[PDB]
Length: 425
Ligand SMILES: OC[C@H]1O[C@H](O[C@H]2[C@H](O)[C@@H](O)[C@@H](O[C@H]3[C@H](O)[C@@H](O)[C@@H](O[C@H]4[C@H](O)[C@@H](O)[C@@H](O[C@H]5[C@H](O)[C@@H](O)[C@H](O)O[C@@H]5CO)O[C@@H]4CO)O[C@@H]3CO)O[C@@H]2CO)[C@H](O)[C@@H](O)[C@@H]1O
Ligand SMILES: [Ca+2]
Ligand SMILES: [Ca+2]
Ligand SMILES: [Ca+2]
Image 1 (tube, helix red, strand yellow):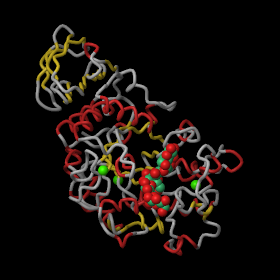
Image 2 (cartoon, helix red, strand yellow):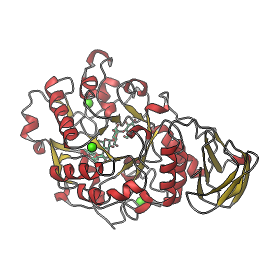
Image 3 (tube, protein in one colour):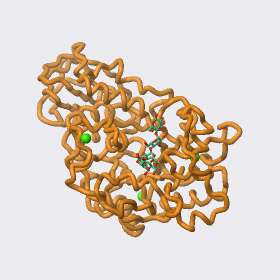
Image 4 (cartoon, rainbow, N blue to C red):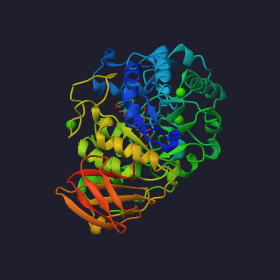
């Protein structure tokens, strides 16, 4: 229900949830078995399109104007502080999405607070060659003004913001566009930006480093955890073909070890961006996806709270607005069961397989303690596989059903499009 550390638990991405909504849905998030929560950017941003709350305006939260805490979309610093305290009341940790690689693109909106720092930016010359580290780190991403991360004065300014969040109650960070901030060994233009701003009391901290050739996943891993963006793609592909074949969904598609990895089925971008890369999915595809990644060992899964009514190609249904609580899926019986499972199996090794050679059925056996089954198939299946679980009756915790282990053999009917969580007590 609550792991001994942010790293051993499941993180709920409260995408666009205001500080007050969060505060109010704390008992629920605790009940659902999450150890940490990830908020949207908590700082002062360029509140575009006249500050309108339509979900389609979500992107304005990634265009900072000053690094003061509080904004119209999510709320005020006091509210943030109050929410961190409400979280702590149930042992929940708070993770802050820190957009520290850039500010807004609208130069006139940038605060004096920012403009006062001598030589604070690199400019807004759009990145051209993505295979070039110099271009990727030293130039403008989307025309968003690029902070001059080599400037110790900007480092200090940005770091005091992190410090302030931690002191407000926060416990960790998700470094937005962390791939666009050079490392020490990043050639002639490296810097001590990471060793510096990473040196805080933050329990857990990881960066969004979308994978490619100039992303250096294994290098950033030496400072913070990294995002397995490719793996997420493998998962979505699997769910797409309804083929949960272990050969493909077992390699994290990265050269970083899973204990320095943050995983997901989809991110706020794949869903919310105009590409609609993962919007196609439905709650059912997400349940099976979660079962697959949140049953793994060592990797920290991040659950994405989609807009009330989103899915099936529909991004912004217009049933909620920025600040409103997301869909109820975050606390579904099947999701909750896997979170609990994920927590209790901490430390346990894993072994993946496909019962009876059926690639539509995913089985994850954590030691001789638990078993997670995911049937992506459109029909029900009766299984009969070996098991390290003791003999006895096991009721499906993720939903309805019972399985019987007998003479080291698992048997039962996993319902179509269903997840099954199996373990004692
Ligand atoms: O006015 C400038 C700009 O404003 C808007 O742009 C929006 C984006 O549309 C929103 O997506 C958002 O962007 C955020 C993301 O939400 C945030 O998660 C993160 O994502 C970045 C990555 O960090 C960055 O690396 C890059 O990903 C690349 C990979 O690097 C590359 O390997 C792979 O091949 O391709 C991906 C995608 O190109 O880009 C993503 C975002 O797509 O950081 C960004 C920046 O904060 O917010 C911005 C700004 O509000 C308008 O939509 C846009 O048209 C306009 O140019
Ligand atoms: Ca940069
Ligand atoms: Ca805290
Ligand atoms: Ca659509």
